[PDB]
Image (cartoon, rainbow, N blue to C red; front, side, top):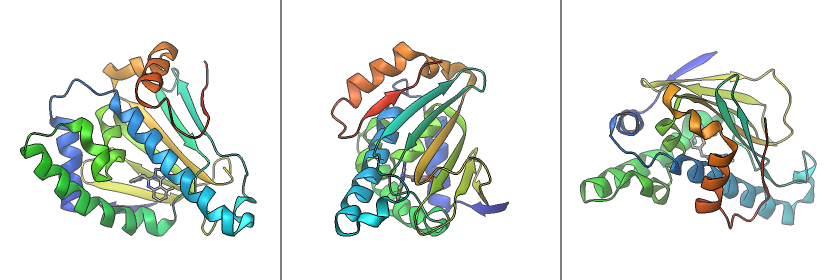
Length: 207
Ligand SMILES: Nc1nc2c3c(F)cccc3nc(Cc3ccc4c(c3)OCO4)n2n1
């Protein structure tokens, strides 16, 4: 297990998301589905010039998996997936300029729901999750598990769980008072409201 410090700017973003009073938390789901859609567009596009990039799986989809026993909501996609370099360096680089833009917008009168427009919607997971684990596999790299409970650090390890083929699983370890996002009716409401035109099938698993 390797431990890394977030850049100060990303840490500050995560603290803002965790600390600001903001009742409209449900938007986290829209943001992670949008992230999945983006990742799926990428593999779909790349597969047009190189069909063998789909040898790791042809199905392009998003699954939403609630688990009351574990108190987790998992968003799974079969998108392009993330490399170790993404996890350690690249995502952070993109997040830095986005965080700065988002911060300035917020002071100008924007709200937290506009986070996605700045390319840092992933961190909205921390509206509802005390801990986020991300399992991811890109065609050019190994399966990795990224994990953070914020506090300024994240971990990366090689994953030895079930091999996933290709894509990303975002596992939300929900805060004690945010278990509404495990309820079938609540998840369906949120998807219908914010994600109804996503261009990939979204399957909400039942318990
Ligand atoms: N599902 C999914 N696939 C991608 C992704 C991807 F598949 C390729 C490149 C970048 C990506 N960025 C994100 C957003 C993201 C940002 C920061 C993160 C993260 C995911 O996981 C750990 O830190 N996602 N989310």
